[PDB]
Length: 297
Image (cartoon, rainbow, N blue to C red; front, side):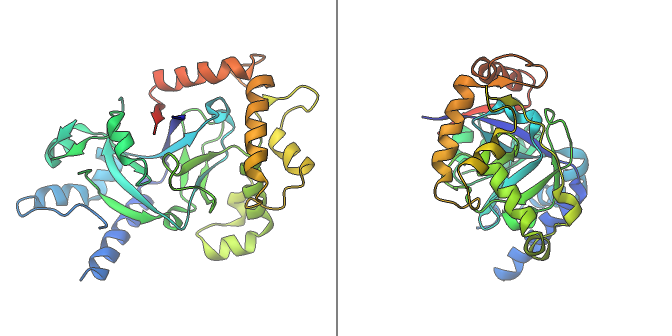
């Protein structure tokens, strides 16, 4: 049972998120002339409350639930990765970690979470989302539609963390949304490098512009005799060919263990602390500050 740290990844432009939301509602009503929980006969006021700009701008926070095994690197986050080819679910949940009626969920849950199907019942077991009297689904949206949205966390140095596509995200692991920390992760580095290299493919295919692809990731971890920016260092040394290179999984596992046992933190509030210790503190601080959750499956 692997423990993950979920980080609250807030959406900057909630009105654009609302456009995406209503575009999806309309598409699904058209095709079905499984995307959202149906509204019952006397629930029109609920429908009118949810399908409303106020719901996304005033009433609720819109939050992608990012999953990481390296929470100590969150200050360096430069992008948010999503699987563009898979469906993500929108569901209401709690800000702090529950069989409830639709009305009760609307009245009690301040956050709209975006996450994979895989995560849903795990989240409910963790007390992060309620069960409906079986999960209340506001929408189901392919990841491609979120590519280019601006996100941020309360930990990240920068606040323009665009959503980028990563097709190697496995839908059976956690929430299927991951923080991009390109300085400190070879897979993140690899994916960002492929996007940059094939910027014409990516900006043609998705709602992405060249100028969005230049965000720096502040390295949080130095390795003795290597230095910082270890993601790039192992990308280059192991001759990684792309973010879909079969050897990455092993490189990712080796680098994870090496940073954990040997890394030194290079960012506030952890400067000079060993990564081994910081892993635990960062989990503590993130949870205590209500910036995220512990999650198991």
